[PDB]
Amino acid sequence: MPYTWKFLGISKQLSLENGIAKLNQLLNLEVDLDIQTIRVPSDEYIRYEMRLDYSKFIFLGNSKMEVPMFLCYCGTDNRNEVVLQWLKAEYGVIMWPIKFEQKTMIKLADASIVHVTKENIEQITWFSSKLYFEPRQFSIEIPRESCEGLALGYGTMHPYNDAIVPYIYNETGMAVERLPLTSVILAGHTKIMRESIVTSTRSLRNRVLAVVLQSIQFT
Image 1 (cartoon, helix red, strand yellow):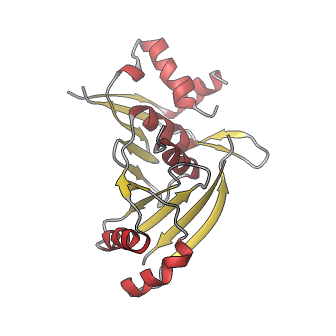
Image 2 (cartoon, one colour):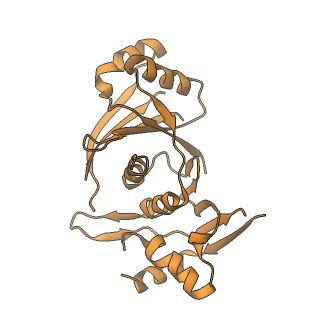
């Protein structure tokens, strides 16, 4: 699974359109910038995407929220740090690494598979689900099919939190909420850890970005 994403909170909402030419002349490249207003049914976000020349930056902003924006990136390129420092210098923002608490990791898991269609209908792309724990180590795995049945047995928009985790407690006596979760793995799709997210394709779901931005809010 090729793409490891890191996350930085940003102290101010940035309009990258305004600063981009400076970044181009600094890197000697013509950076590709894409700007999209997105809606995540439940609010509305501004999403920037930035491709250099496998190095990629994604930004999610919301004017209504106290922490208005964060960015994430993937790739191991030398120039990632150039972009970060450039951001700090050009905009005087304060940027900090984001770490996901356990409850957040479960939400990110839900956000990775759940989505809503045009006619406002819940859909879920199910994958085999592995939870790792480190008290020395062990893991529990639920194949795709039982996930799917367990979920349709329930009402959803939070299948891991409303179906899978309770089914685990109710059928095995293991309380996921009481154990030291280290990662959630959705086979062929995504790996959610405390300090990063790994993906199989070169992007993160919009709902996942939304959940990140909401998790870094101060109270």
